[PDB]
Image (cartoon, rainbow over all chains, first blue to last red):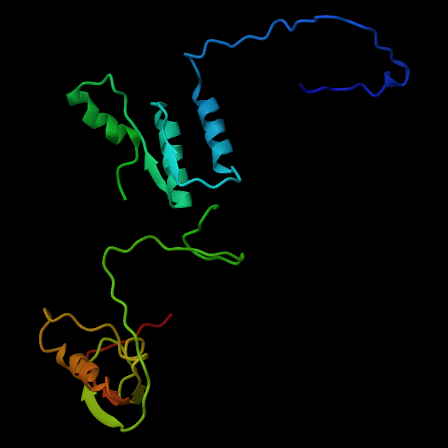
Length: 106
Length: 104
């Protein structure tokens, strides 16, 4: 729990005995459709984490922008990176997707 | 751990350059027991003036060794390198007539 207080009226405020007040309205949206902005924001959060780690994991993103941002993190901190391509692709379609990731090069 | 830069600027930090697939590291030492002299042709150097070369200066002074594919232009630098492992010396550079230097 966290609380927020209004400074105008707390000079004269009262509290009474209440029982079993239940929270309502808290929902999780459709999580199968998440924009790339959320992934980029969370990658930016991960970059400035004050903790120390020695590996970066894809964890099933399958988004090219997020993958290349994670690769930039790996090249910045000098650590290892383990990324994955979509497993539902066939053998013939897997090869172009690697170039589509944008990590190929030097 | 935190971010690591590739090159230094003006801020205070430690930087590591990217890994180089091919390069050579050379160590030098100075000694002046005896002094030698000679004449050669090199990539760069002030012509017709006496130049003093040590083990740590024979690359900056003089210059990068000339490729053997050019032919008959590489022997002097190899001779200087062989002779400089003991003591330093003096070299005078000779240049052909059709040589020019830039100016703006």
